[PDB]
Amino acid sequence: MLIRKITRKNPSPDVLEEAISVMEGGGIVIYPTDTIYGLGVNALDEDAVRRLFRVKGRSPHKPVSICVSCVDEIPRFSRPSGDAMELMERILPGPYTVVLERNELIPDVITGGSSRVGIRVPDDEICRRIAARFPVTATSANISGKPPSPRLEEIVRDLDAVDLVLDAGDCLDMEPSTVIDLTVNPPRVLRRGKGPLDPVLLRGAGDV
């Protein structure tokens, strides 16, 4: 061979075959990242619409958030722009969610009762590969009750085959979380910060 080409069969680790396994059984898969517990499942599957109302259970008119590798992975998936993609291309990836417009997608079960769709670019290396090709559902597991589990063995125990746990686990801090609604030119970068008491750069070494 002369030119540097690509192989045929791609290596599939243990975690890779484990994720596609539960997906075959039509179940929900969770995955925490730099922020808190996240959710990932076959978005183009009816199983996602069902497990969606279970977590939220508010109004079927609100759009849903999905997961992908990058803007290049979701071309004809969403509606992007020039300077718009530039703003996000500046500080990406990260534990922030990217909400954009919606393409000519017919399924209103994912697009919601509006013409907008959410996206999320986490630091999950594995989820980055799968989401790159086939898109997945990305929802934050932190609704009413105790959605985020503290023990990996606790999830597999309760949800025998419902909410399949993860082999990778979390990534960074359990909190907080950033939410950006990058629609068009005007970006809605809105991080969930604290009250008016940001750490100044004054002189203070006596923390005691």
Image (cartoon, grey):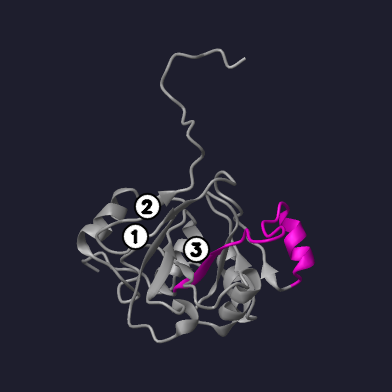
Give x and y (percent) for residue 61: 50, 77
Dot 2 amino acid type:
Val
Asked whether the residues under the numbered discs 1 and 2 touch, taking CB atoms below 8 Å apart as contact, a structural biologist would say yes
Label 1 and label 2: CA atoms lie apart by: 7 Å
Secondary structure category for the residue under label 2: strand
Give x and y (percent) for residue 196: 47, 34
Q: Looking at the picture, does residue 204 appear above or below residue 49? A: above
Q: Looking at the picture, does residue 89 appear above or below residue 193? A: below
Q: Looking at the picture, does residue 78 appear above or below residue 34? A: below
Image quarter where the N terminus lies is bottom left
Q: Which residue is mark 3?
A: 127
Characterize the local packing of mark 1: few (<14), some (14-19) or many (20 or more) Cα atoms within 10 angstroms. Answer: many
Label 2 and label 3: CA atoms lie apart by: 23 Å
Residue at the image point whose x is 51% and y is 50% from the top: 177
Q: Which mark is residue 182?
A: 1
Q: Which mark is residue 189?
A: 2
* Earlier residue among tags 1 and 3: 3
Dot 1 amino acid type:
Leu
Residue stretch rendered in magenta on the structure:
135-160
